Amino acid sequence: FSEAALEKKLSELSNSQQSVQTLSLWLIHHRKHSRPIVTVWERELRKAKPNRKLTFLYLANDVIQNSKRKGPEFTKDFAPVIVEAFKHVSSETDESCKKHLGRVLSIWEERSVYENDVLEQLKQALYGLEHHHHHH
Image (cartoon, rainbow, N blue to C red; front, side, top):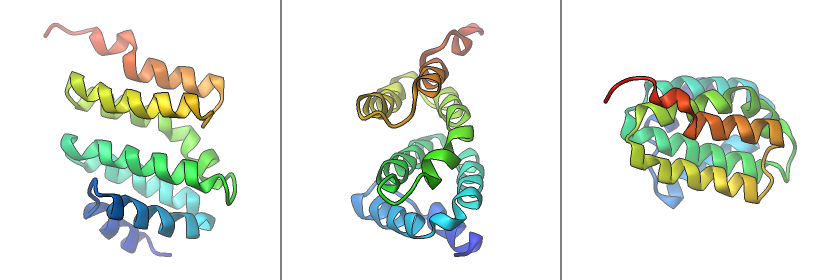
């Protein structure tokens, strides 16, 4: 595992099934490094252009869900950053992009991906009144 390799892969990440699936497999293989991986993922997410940010969440979705079979590493290590990540993506993208964020969150609530406390925080992050403080 190297952070440099991860950075390179994240920079060339796209929405294709092959792009997300292969990166997910690599990350899960390297689950011993889940904390540094999440740290790098969060940093590159914030650096990404709005039209690319959703792709980071799709990756996280795939990694978190598929990792559960192997261990709790990714579920646990995404947990402290994932609310802020949804809030970030929600704020930096067009209102209609909530279609995609909401789909993921719906998936997570339907498949029990995180517990209640977290799921509700995610709900607030996505739909909450804090997005509506300023005239537009």
